Length: 206
Length: 211
Image: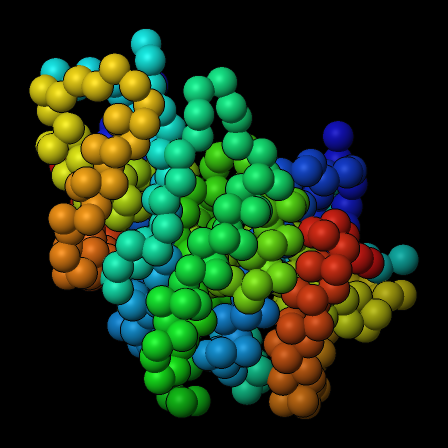
């Protein structure tokens, strides 16, 4: 049985074992960061379906890569082209190129997805990326979902797009219209979130 | 399933079991490369000691670190460890750590490497580690080749226990004590400062076993 949390499908009631993994990771991150601060090294990412009609249907999947410094790279996935480990690998590799030019980094993302397989992992290892521990079923702890994609939504409400290029202009209008303070905030809010999780002994706190 | 290094690990790792082992080793190597953390590790695991060694048994637990033994403890037969008891165990282990460290310049903050797969690793245990400021290193399921206790200490034990029989628990226990006391401080350092190379191999082997 499932429920939608931050647009992501998640247990209608976490198991005891699922709250332990959340508490354990949250606790350790809070401690890690207090002793050896790393928030400012975090690169994070997720995907969101953008619906052509914001009141089956038609929609386009976007992927965004960002850090507290600001946006790094987003791309769109063409309708009917479900993404694979080897292209994600690609995505990663040019994400890294754009980053280098702005400028080791630490990646925070949902590791429990398909395109997160050997080629992908290979790429990150190869490129020198440490992946941050992340408890299963925890959208509340991924900044793209609790921050970025949430504000995107407020921006998307009541919008009808006709062509793909329109959606993309709405997204890109949105991301590009964002201050660096917007990204800085998404990331630096993590510590509070880890704490809030711990206090809830690993349950959802919002 | 099938036993490896004493513990029940599958015959074939599903493709992600091997992915997780890769994801962690890669990250741990990288993290250690950016900010060395080995010498802050405190590791521990549990092992049914057997009465004749070439059924009656006695479970032993050992906490240690690259600097030495910290604390070990036996569980009589018939007794099961409770998350609360384990929590108490941690609190005791911790107190020894600080006497051992009380000697130093700056204690740095301990990173526990241990098997969270156990069942007595639950809220009470988690609460205690948190309450004590203990970081917990990530650990891939079914990966005894990565816990030093299992691959280093417990291995050299089977190697000193072989062809030995005792007809009482105190006498088993006594054997263990004899062993760990005859280990010099850099026998422990070696179990720890060996992880890097063990992580790598897991990576070079794309998340599979390597011995």
